[PDB]
Length: 122
Image (cartoon, one colour):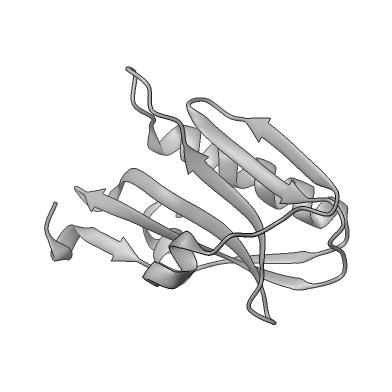
């Protein structure tokens, strides 16, 4: 995978930073794993992701995480390794579930320019 097909919204530090859930919820959407801290409310959030793009659209997700304006990780979608792989639809489902959960607790979720461009496109 080249750098003309590799989007890194997240720094190395961001990708690997440990984060804890006061009120943990976890879900599975396809071969994907979803995490929100249910303790978070009333914040602006931004979903950022690292992933590879082919034929103008997301191919493989490495990691997505939810960031408060303050710079804190309040959620995550992550790939489980399995034989099917995982599809752009899995990812797009996962994102809707993340977003749904975040807003349910009165947060406002935005998605990165690149996730708009390649996955959350319409």
